[PDB]
Length: 99
Length: 274
Length: 9
Ligand SMILES: *[C@@H]1O[C@H](CO[C@H]2O[C@@H](C)[C@@H](O)[C@@H](O)[C@@H]2O)[C@@H](O[C@@H]2O[C@H](CO)[C@@H](O)[C@H](O)[C@H]2NC(C)=O)[C@H](O)[C@H]1NC(C)=O
Ligand SMILES: *[C@@H]1O[C@H](CO)[C@@H](O)[C@H](O)[C@H]1NC(C)=O
Image: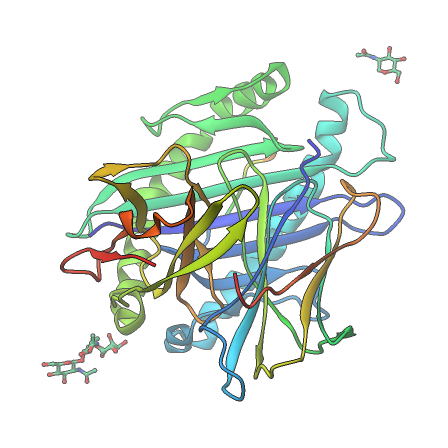
């Protein structure tokens, strides 16, 4: 089965400039399992990102979380880039702090 | 309340790139606690929760040996299925398995299960009676016949009623501070404009544990579960969860809609508005 | 404690 991934980007705590927080990129409902996930700060790859919570649902689609500690500022931007066979090109989803 | 111990296993072939990738991830309830990944340079079963520091070196050695054995059996399974389905060796294929047991508040077994899938489709599964298997196609029927002659269900039933339940009880005891805790949700509502004098109201629930939660939107005492949009409950990176649910309403009438949050950590459900 | 021996398909 070929299922396109849903990509969700969100912080642990409501964002407040200057205060430590956690940024998450949850990639879900995909198949096959092969996939590439990267988190970016101002367009540059964030090193030491942690991958966790890998699982699958009743219909067998895959789920996995990418997360990292961060201290937001008014103008730093963050995003999650994902590459999967179901898509022609990599998909980049930005963190929307006003969602 | 009830608790569960689950193991998610995945084997993925990759022709022309070496051996299949093999992974095992274990969970107590909705908390990841152990993991094995064949693609690390020194594949070993590793702790994923702080309380697992309470197990000795022998525990890790034994789990690691089991994982390496499992890795080899699934490697063989991938070849066998190419035969059952008359497929070529040039493409990538996936085998997935979910195994687990669940106990009640008193620690006694409520149910057990083990289900397999090939390329994202049901293959074979253990029936509720823990005595027979049910096959999704003719290939799985061959497997069913093999397992009946080998007594596979009896061996798995013994694991469920003994080992699985006993260790789940131990994990709940050792990690009580983490697993039996309750973190109350903190909520808020965001507002967004849209085309045609309408507005999007989004209700957020943050920092809670366990994961089970209910979020609803009401209008004059009636739930709008229909025209409501939402995301599946998701992990937030520190052992807690979050979720949001939204509804579209007429501009200037936002005050007539209320979000309701029900959770184990809320003696009285939360009611809030924009 | 993980399952110990997954029977071959
Ligand atoms: C979680 O349970 C502990 C008791 O169990 C702790 O010690 C070992 C037996 C082992 O299971 C270990 O993993 C676990 O952390 C509770 O602590 C006890 O609390 C009572 C309160 O009356 C004290 O009298 C005991 O001395 C104390 N035992 C210990 C740890 O020395 C602990 O309270 C509980 N966690 C929570 C929710 O607070
Ligand atoms: C298996 O597939 C090949 C073509 O890929 C075909 O020649 C052969 O007859 C098939 N055998 C079966 C069991 O259908």
